[PDB]
Amino acid sequence: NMSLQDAEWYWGDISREEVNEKLRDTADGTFLVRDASTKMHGDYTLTLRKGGNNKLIKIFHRDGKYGFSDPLTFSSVVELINHYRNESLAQYNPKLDVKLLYPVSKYQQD
Amino acid sequence: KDSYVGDEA
């Protein structure tokens, strides 16, 4: 019973400009997820740092599954992210050879 | 720059 709301790297309805505040100046493989710019289908947007730029990868949501491209194979956003911590996004696009290495946490350090 | 990444080349 994992909830996306508890994910360190899930920042909800923040904007791309707000994401850039968190990803600017970071290392390759730094990442967070926000809601997509539009609510259609309940998609999400992964933002991943590479080469000093922010790469945005749509997380499609269809029929209760999630993925970057068809076929959608993941049962939750958390499961998707956990997969790409270990497997490079070269699986999505051969030219995007980066893993999800450094989550940007929304929580205070306490 | 913020860029969407597509699945084609």
Image (spheres, coloured by chain):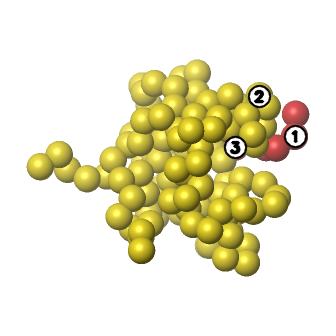
For label 3, the SS is: strand
Instruction: Name the subunit of mark 3.
Output: B
Give the position of the N terminus of chain A as an image quadrant. Answer: bottom left
Q: What is the crowding at mark 3: few (fewer than 14 residues within 10 Å), some, or many (at least 20)?
A: some
Pointer 1: what residue? B8
Q: Position of residue A58 (x, y in %)?
A: 67, 54
Question: For chain B, what colour was chosen?
Answer: red
Q: Amino acid at mark 2?
A: Lys
State the mark number for residue B4: 3
The crowd level at tag 1 (other Cα within 10 Å; few <14, some 14-19, many 20+) is few
Disc 3 to disc 2, how far (Cα)?
Answer: 13 Å
The answer to whether A68 is drawn above or below residue A85 in the figure is: below
Q: Is residue A64 shown left or right of residue A95? A: left
Query: In terms of depth relative to the viewer, which is nearer, A94 or A43?
Result: A94
What's the distance in space between the residues labelled 1 and 3, CA to CA? 12 Å
Residue indicated by mark 2: A95
* Between marks 1 and 3 in the image, the one whose residue lies nearer the viewer: 1
State the image quarter where residue A12 is shown.
Answer: bottom left
| Residue at x 65%, y 35% (from the top left corner) | A88
Q: Residue A38, how many percent across, how many down?
A: 63, 67
In front: A3, or A43? A3
Q: Tell me the chain of label 1.
A: B
* Farthest-out residue, top: A51
Chain rendered yellow: A
- Amino acid type at image mark 3: Tyr
Q: Which mark is residue A1?
A: none
Residue A104 location, quadrant: top left
Examine the rendering and report whether any part of residue A93 can be seen.
yes
- Contact check, label 3 and label 2, Cβ < 8 Å: no
Q: Residue A75, position in %: x, y?
A: 62, 68
